[PDB]
Image: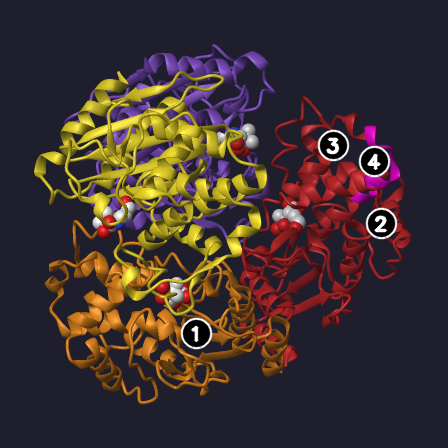
Chain colours: A orange, B red, C purple, D yellow
């Protein structure tokens, strides 16, 4: 019957919608189009940081990286301002998470090295976490104007949940680094209207958003109940029907979170 | 399956639980022990104010009412301070709602007049709103130490919902007065951890709480969705199992509200 | 010329206003009626907690304290709810700071012992910190209806600043305890509209408010610049002119903080 | 007093600093190097939009403009992506304000027509608003890399304030258009750490930034007090001392705004 409540939101908001919450000690998993493909958008920036955290020691975040005016092809609210000054890996990661800065993302991919501009290195990282399905070829901005049906630059709710789970809750990173990533996500600016707004205030929520064309809108998060019980929530949507220029509806993502909060409480 | 989620909370929290939300233009009502009797506790102070608003002109709120130090039997954080000075009907109502002042309650019942200390007059008022089941017999504090099963000083979730609906949303009161009551409930101090904490912040919530012995804990509220859709939510509980001195669990009330928010979103 | 800006606010808001910030390594202090007496209101609850932290070991916070329904004479949003269950010293302190609970305050004074209900014990504590001027005689609620000119239950901005400085920044408490107090103040609920609202968001602010009759309104705080430079800010006001029933203006407190932020930046 | 506080910031940050706030119904203006020349940087994009709003009817914003890959000389986060699709005047203006897109800027100058690439047409527009000092000669990127002392592509705080005032507050534009421009500025992405960060959150702020070599960093804004009183704030800086390669300090701009907020409150 929760299936039917998601299908309702789908109809109201004129969108296809994908939801995954893994199982726990107590609870059974929650599936809805969980094994269908969706566009990543900016959601892959979460693991990306983790990949950079994984590859290098912890003092590596101090390395300053320089770049040019014509390195800014994507929207980049932080990179734009620090062309003269440059930016350290540390600041790059902060921005990529907290502000969804597109340029930084690309710089960090380059920090991974390897062909594809570091997209292979990163693809490789996901496999280390047992992620077969997710696939990534292009960078920002080009990847977020790929057409519907195209399986390049895509993932499933099921998949990305299990990644985020291993990173945050699992032992995929040392505690010190893990800490950093949570801290960053805990302070995301771009996610107020989506998963955060669907949960009660007494729940703790850390999230990473994704947006694009064809009404594409995603949010992946870890939440803690008022008694500190952790849960992973992958929410993904699109509106490929209204074409390229369709607007995403955060309201959709907020409403679903509320249904989910209901079963989890 | 929502039936099964309430029965779960019941088992977790070792409590009996009553829930009612009336039907709307779209949605069907939500019932769970909705037609079972529970203790009012301090929840009856909401209609009580309405009864005093209903019976008298609007300038009647300026009438000063004096009382003694030994008129303070219940918890009365506001009555305590204004013993020498007295208090106007207006300020009495504010206190009764916003602070759940027990003395004021009794003063207002006396303002209704009639035997029972004004409990019959008040019982009479509810019938004017088509409320058959509800009964009120004693005053504060004595009423909050009635034993389980005793039908004096009781109501059903179903009933009190339909009252609150008529008062707040319906035309049971002139707009000016209606306004006052909503304003007061909007500014309740005593309700943070119950219904308010079960809904997302982007919902508007006005509530009136109740507490007592045998783990008795109630909260009735009107909520607005993020798009201004109103709903009435009656939640009532008790824990007569652990006897007189069983502690109430607000956690229970907050958790249920969350399940409810889930179906309403 | 900052003198003239405070006198302006005074005239606009029809209020007397007291401001103190101590001197630092760099900066000179800020004075305006800093050595004039004002009512404490709920501001004394900050040191009060410190006095209880000072007097007893750290394990003492687990001692559960019981009380009756008629022990709630003041407004007490948390004491209200935990009459059946009781409350530990630890929880009492949290409430007294975070919610300005009036009852708890009085219970804690009783924990200090001595005549005056523990007001002498507490008065004694301030002298240990070299505070000459500050005086405390009555408890809640009686102290909040002292008339203007009455020097009982009063302090100066200068004084209370130097206390708060020693507690938070100075070595007046062991680090562990100090930590607790800061944590509590960092999470004050009652202070959003006063000092907090006069500083830019990139400043860190921890505060403790006070309100009462005769438009009495205070806020004492520690702030950190965006680069972690600490400062102590005492702000106090009243409007004894419009009599007992004069309303306090938080706007006044927020405006002054802004003038202060200006010199500190 | 305040003169000396600006000279301090100057010394701290190793920079020359220009500040202007016009006079109001109440307050006297604020001058500090207000009549000295500074580089525009990207600040001129504000009036530029206004000039295009002024010259043409309101439906002109729908005219699509196409361009080539080799038309993208400057930083252009939006122009980069819409080479295939093209962009309407409407979208061009949004970008120029909200994202400080450098290409769009140049396209719009071309929309004005005339020699200099439309820089004379634009220079001409400012004179219509009674602005004598301001001049513009080159386009992006070339204009941001021309040396200190060179009076081409420059303005004074005094001047640009009086322009922004007339546009936003004054009757320089019809309400409908005026509305558009404010809306755009209200939604600037590039300005978080400058003027916006120096004011308290309860102030409303709309801004337009500028950055360049020789530590050049500007922000012009309209602010509303918490009670809706409007003010215009021009802040400009540079660090020609450390030569071409000197890094700009937004911190400087944020600090000054704080001093200004202080006098305005
Ligand atoms: C991540 O969610 C995407 C970042 N930004 C894009 C979006 O649609 O939100 C763009 C297209 C603005 S970016 O220039 O690629
Ligand atoms: C409203 O919920 C009831 C308040 N009653 C109190 C009273 O003093 O009458 C108590 C203490 C009996 S109950 O614990 O709320
Ligand atoms: C802090 O001590 C202020 C207390 N005074 C008032 C308040 O704001 O709580 C009263 C007078 C309402 S107190 O609770 O009696
Ligand atoms: C406007 O001030 C922005 C101009 N863009 C850049 C350019 O390449 O011209 C800079 C370097 C001046 S700015 O640092 O973003």
Residues B33 and D163: in front is D163
Find the distance from the CA under tag 1 to the CA under tag 3: 49 Å
- Asked if the residue at tag 1 contacts the one at tag 2, i.e. Cβ–Cβ closer than 8 Å, the answer is no
Residues A20 and D218: in front is D218
Specify the subunit that label 4 lies on.
B
Label 3: few (<14), some (14–19) or many (≥20) C-alpha neighbours in 10 Å: some
- Asked if the residue at tag 3 contacts the one at tag 1, i.e. Cβ–Cβ closer than 8 Å, the answer is no
Comparing labels 4 and 3, the label whose residue is closer to the camera: 3
Main secondary structure along the magenta-highlighted residues? helix
User: Mark 1 highlights which residue?
Assistant: A233
- Element under label 3? helix
- Element under label 4? helix
Q: Ligand 3: does it lie within 8 Å of the C-beta at label 3?
A: no
- Element under label 2? loop
User: Mark 4 highlights which residue?
Assistant: B111
Look at 56% across and 68% down and name the residue there. Answer: A255
Label 1: few (<14), some (14–19) or many (≥20) C-alpha neighbours in 10 Å: many
User: Mark 3 highlights which residue?
Assistant: B90
Q: Residue furthest left?
A: D242
């Amino acid at each position: 019957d929760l299936a039917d409540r998601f299908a309702e939101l789908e109809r109201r908001y004129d969108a296809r919608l994908g939801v995954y919450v893994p199982a726990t000690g107590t609870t059974a998993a929650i599936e809805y189009r969980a094994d269908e493909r969706f566009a990543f958008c900016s959601t892959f920036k979460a693991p990306l940081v983790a990949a950079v955290l994984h590859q290098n020691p912890l003092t590596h975040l101090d390395k300053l990286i320089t770049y040019t005016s014509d390195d800014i092809r994507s929207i980049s609210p932080v990179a734009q301002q620090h062309v003269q000054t440059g930016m350290t890996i540390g600041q790059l990661c902060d921005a990529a998470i907290r502000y969804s800065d597109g340029t930084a993302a690309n710089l960090l991919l380059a920090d991974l090295g390897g062909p594809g501009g570091g997209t292979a290195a990163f693809t490789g990282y996901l496999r280390s976490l047992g992620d077969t399905v997710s696939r990534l070829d292009a960078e920002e901005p080009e990847l977020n104007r790929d057409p519907p049906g195209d399986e390049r630059d895509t993932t499933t709710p099921h998949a990305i949940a299990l990644v985020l789970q291993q990173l945050v809750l699992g032992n995929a990173l040392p505690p010190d680094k893990r800490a950093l990533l949570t801290d960053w996500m805990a302070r995301n600016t771009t996610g107020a209207k989506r998963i955060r707004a669907g949960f009660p205030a007494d729940w703790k929520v850390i999230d990473k958003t994704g947006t694009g064309d064809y009404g594409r809108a995603n949010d992946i998060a870890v939440v803690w109940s008022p008694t500190g019980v952790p849960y992973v929530v992958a929410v993904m949507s699109d509106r490929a029907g209204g074409g390229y220029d369709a607007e995403p509806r955060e309201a959709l993502l907020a409403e679903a979170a509320t249904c989910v909060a209901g079963v989890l409480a």
